[PDB]
Image (cartoon, rainbow, N blue to C red):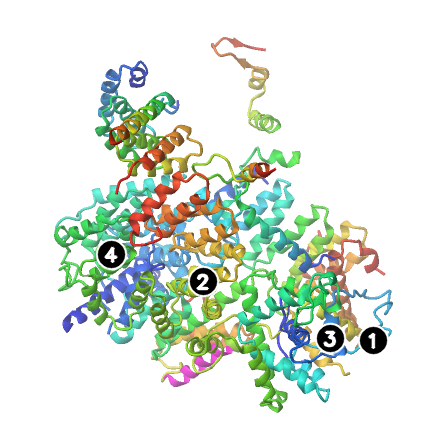
Amino acid sequence: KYGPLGITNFITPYDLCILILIHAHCSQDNGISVPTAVFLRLISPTRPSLEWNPLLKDNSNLRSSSIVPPPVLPILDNIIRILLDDKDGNKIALTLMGYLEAINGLDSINRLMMDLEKNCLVNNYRSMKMRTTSTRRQMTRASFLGTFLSTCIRKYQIGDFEMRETIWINLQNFKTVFKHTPLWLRFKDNVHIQKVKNCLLANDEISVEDQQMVEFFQHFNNGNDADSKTMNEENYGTLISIQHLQSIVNRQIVNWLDYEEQSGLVFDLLDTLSLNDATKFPLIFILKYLEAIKENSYQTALDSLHNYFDYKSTGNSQNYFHISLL
Amino acid sequence: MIRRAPTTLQLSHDDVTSLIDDLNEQKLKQQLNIE
Amino acid sequence: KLDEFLMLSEQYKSRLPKIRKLGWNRFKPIGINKTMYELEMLRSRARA
Amino acid sequence: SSSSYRDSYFQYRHLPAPHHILYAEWNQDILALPDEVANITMAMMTSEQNSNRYWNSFHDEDDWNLFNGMELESNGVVTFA
Amino acid sequence: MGVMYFKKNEFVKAKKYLKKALEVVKDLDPSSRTTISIQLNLGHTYRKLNENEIAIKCFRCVLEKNDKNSEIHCSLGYLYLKTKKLQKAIDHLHKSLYLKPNNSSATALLKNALELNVTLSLD
Amino acid sequence: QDKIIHDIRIQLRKAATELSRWKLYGSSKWAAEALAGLAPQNGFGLSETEYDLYLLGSTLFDAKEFDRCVFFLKDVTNPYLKFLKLYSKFLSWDKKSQESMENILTTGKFTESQSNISSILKEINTFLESYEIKIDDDEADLGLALLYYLRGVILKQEKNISKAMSSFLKSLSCYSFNWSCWLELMDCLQKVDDALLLNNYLYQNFQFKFSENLGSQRTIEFNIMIKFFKLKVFEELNGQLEDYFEDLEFLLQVFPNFTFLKAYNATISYNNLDYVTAESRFDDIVKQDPYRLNDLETYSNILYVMQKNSKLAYLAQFVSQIDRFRPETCCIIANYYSARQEHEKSIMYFRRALTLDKKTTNAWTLMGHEFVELSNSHAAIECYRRAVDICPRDFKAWFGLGQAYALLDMHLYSLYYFQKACTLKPWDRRI
Amino acid sequence: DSQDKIIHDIRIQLRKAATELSRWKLYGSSKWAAEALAGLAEAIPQNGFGLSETEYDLYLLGSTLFDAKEFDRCVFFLKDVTNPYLKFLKLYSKFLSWDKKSQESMENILTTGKFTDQSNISSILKEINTFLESYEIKIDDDEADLGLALLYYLRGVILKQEKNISKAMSSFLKSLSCYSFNWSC
Amino acid sequence: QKNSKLAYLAQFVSQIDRFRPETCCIIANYYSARQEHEKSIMYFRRALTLDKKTTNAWTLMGHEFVELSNSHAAIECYRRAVDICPRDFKAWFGLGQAYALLDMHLYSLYYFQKACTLKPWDRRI
């Protein structure tokens, strides 16, 4: 599940996983309602901003009155283990499994984006009651999922075709990583995957001519390894937004200071940053600073401490020099 | 010592308007013969 | 702290109409001595 | 058709990096001319006097004195101050 | 001296002196505002003399010497408009308006060319 | 066939190497690629004190330091080493020679002029006039053809088409089997009746220099690419065809699995508006040469009419996967945005692709259409105009002006624009 | 005396140095080689390649599609060749295809490196090792051509970009030992 | 110094081409001498983008913030320079001054101490 880590201002493969679930819940054709606990564990880390001063304040507001599950890493292996736990969770997990197999192309990705914006998302509740002819559940902008989906849609119309090409390359890389896992072998055949997959693949408009070469475009791009693969730039294994990364590290440092977490996975990914995300995300430096104090390292701690206060001060327009010295 | 551009003159407005008027004369009289 | 996503979102919103707003003002076709900025101005006065 | 077979103009392969076309606006930048435009930075008629003084610095004392208020009329009659 | 005798509407001695000037300067001054100016003026004198034949060729050679010039194109369109070759003059008018923005006389000539094209019914 | 195909192999081996040697990438790429489809002779006139300059000149050109080549060859008296300097000197001017009004649309920034080539043309004329051996008789060699070719293209820059044809045909007589030379000859037609007149000139007045060429190639009708000349002229504009079908068949028997012929042969179907057969012909090319990207925008254009968006999206993904900054790639991606009714963004990718070549196929016109759906009606008409100036043989460019002026109140201008396109393609029922 | 003899040695070699290196479409040393010869103190063409006419046809296709920026297309046609001279061109086309692609991928990225201070690249490395073992010289022999020496240069540079230092240095020494006067090396 | 000569070089070099890493650093120097900082700051970022190996432009870009009375932006520009290569005496010195201009005298003592090890044999440091 490990891989190079990189901050992305675009649709992470993780973001579509929530988009997959919200599509099944709203469509109400399968009668499958995602449990409210599942959504609150996935969307909530993505919600923007928590903030955390280095010192001078300890868990002033970061502490949650109700104990919360740890945020989930962007690996298909970890997300399924959430849904898989339920006795009927295989039905929910397979729904995500079928959809991720149904989406074999970028156009299919665009199909999901178009479906949600035209029908599912609704500007305000005053038009909700006049849309009683809708066979699918509708969502308000101000709702918990509504404000999330609006950002995701905004985050989709913001980039060019270069943005969407990177979307599909990583997801297949993200998807094929789970294929070489023991969990996938247990789900090699589940008959329900074919049923749910065929629900959305219908109305393909062609089955005799285009599909022979439709396969060719994907297979040639994919690493069939029959010949030397088509040469392409090195691609990151995992894509995470700033807000999602903020929630994992804040949980990690709080947990370290005093549902199981993955200390090994979080630390390895955070060590492969390209040195520009650290500037956009200064808190990665202090995560070393807390660690440096643990082994009682003098020189190592000071460089990290000084580093955290060089990047944070400039980003914040307010003067923060009077906080660095103390 | 430097020479500027020597004096040159182009089609004026009077002569071009006269040619326009003439063009209207021979584009006005011939259709009378056709009709 | 300046949100890099939010600021770059406004940048896209600014540049998007700029393509549609291209033809306004300076551009002048051949055969027409008046630009389309005041084509809609007189058109607005036409109905009103 | 036939697009890349003709080579009679600046093409996409003649420049070293094909991705330099992404910027493609630096060609259309008017570089500031040497001397007098430096006067507009301070300001953010005066520039011409500045250039006049700068070129006036190349005088001898007596020569400068003669030309201190010198004015030459069109018919050639000369006024000395 | 040729422009002088062109101003007084003599149209004869001007042409003679200008031809003398060019035949003096046949060998030298290939470019640089001397051969172009003298040849354009001689063509302009010929248009005023209604001898459009030699005028077409002289304006054409001036044009092939230098392409970016609105006046030469406008005058060539005027010459073609004197005859009936509207198909080969309207393009010149459009390019002339492309080179220089206003060209009010050129705009009038082009418009009249449109009415001419509208009236005519060539196959 | 028999020895005819064998004689082609040897001489085509030449045209592949010297053309690539003296930095003519475009001509050499076709010839070298033609070896693969077809089923080390070295020699030049150079001295040791002058041979270093060629190595000095060639390797700096490859490193794209264009301007330094002119200085380092300031005084060269070699017959054709002079060509590389002037060729480099020409491109050094061209890159900064962007017309102000075309540039505004070309970028959208919205913010010595030409005397250099005037000197370049005079420099070539002075050199040839003072050169030892002229084009007449059995004299001259491969290098002298490049000078006349370089001279001809410069003449076309000043719209001196009448003399441009004489220069190019003069160059082809001295040296044949140069593809880049014939491409510039295509843009010189801009008319239908002159093609048969030029065809008469090739059949009767034109003659080849047998000294440089090999056997069975001095004759016009045993030549193989004179068929290529006839194929290209009769597809850009149909007109009246002479031996078009018969000569096409012979060139198909030779040059097996030659991708350029199949693309041209398939393109004929699109020009005949036979879409169902065109896709099948296009598809076979993709299987054979997946990494050939030339004239793939025609494939995108046919798919646009059928509106098979699912196949087109995958086509865009496949092309963009292996290269992201070639003119046909951005053109295909931009064409994709038209299918999504995102005409407002399709401008950006056409804008990017246009800056790549700035002399493309009918990509200026496709740029213009996207403005019409936005209702600008003023960017499109100016954008349509540029396609006219570059290629006055484009039907869609002329038709675009007439259609746009039809929406405008003044319909007077629409008659002239429609009349020119009427002569170009009288067969269309709509026009 | 002997200095003039040295002078007599350098122009011919630098004529050779600029010939093959430019002939093999690498400009890191070819541009420098002609520069060095131009500044050399004042005091028939030379060419040779062991290529068959059948495979030499692929060279023109390979060489001309190289500088035409279509590196990927060159790889496809030159896949089945076995000559070491051409085998370098295919992998050099393969390597530069990745280098050009990586430049396009990151332009907004100013800082380059890894904070702590592959698989696609490792694909290139295997053909080098696989081809090197199969070929019947494998360096350390008197009869070692320029192409095999030039092959080691690509192996060294592809090793360095993976941060496998202390193995690219040895490869570079082996390449320079068989053929010096390669500035990019 | 001698701005007329620099203005000559800047106009002449820019005429060849504006895509080399160097051609975008020469002009910025010419623009810096004219006290036009919001424009000179632009070319240094431009000069680095063409070739990221030219780390010498990082310290100059940092300096060009200090004259703009923008200490916050300067700190990052200097700090990237040491993160490219820690053995940069120029970057440490330029970062040390930006704190020394402000009242944070002791907070700049570590940076000056680090620069000491790079070039101990200097009176200025």
Mark 1 chain: A
From the image, tell me which residue sits under label 4. F46
Is residue A234 visible to the viewer in this orientation of the structure? no
From the image, tell me which residue sits under label 2. F332
Mark 2 chain: F
Task: Say what secondary structure mark 2 lies in.
Answer: helix
Q: Which residue is drawn at 39% across and 28% down?
A: E105
Verify CB contact (< 8 Å) between mark 3 and mark 4: no
- Depth-wise, is mark 1 or mark 4 nearer the camera? 1
Q: Do labels 4 and 2 share a chain?
A: yes
Question: How many numbered marks does the figure carry?
Answer: 4
- Depth-wise, is mark 4 or mark 2 nearer the camera? 2
The amino acid type found where label 2 is placed reads Ile
Q: What stretch is highlighted in magenta?
A: G122-135
Residue A257 bears which disc, if any? 1
- Depth-wise, is mark 3 or mark 4 nearer the camera? 3
From the image, tell me which residue sits under label 3. A39
Pick the front one: G154 or A159: A159
Please provide percent x and percent y for residue F337. Answer: 51, 61
Please provide percent x and percent y for residue A27. Answer: 65, 74
The amino acid type found where label 4 is placed reads Leu
Distance of label 3 from label 2 (alpha carbons): 40 Å
Q: How crowded is mark 1: few (under 14 residues within 10 Å), some or many (20 or more)?
A: few
Q: Which residue is drawn at 21% across and 46% down?
A: F166
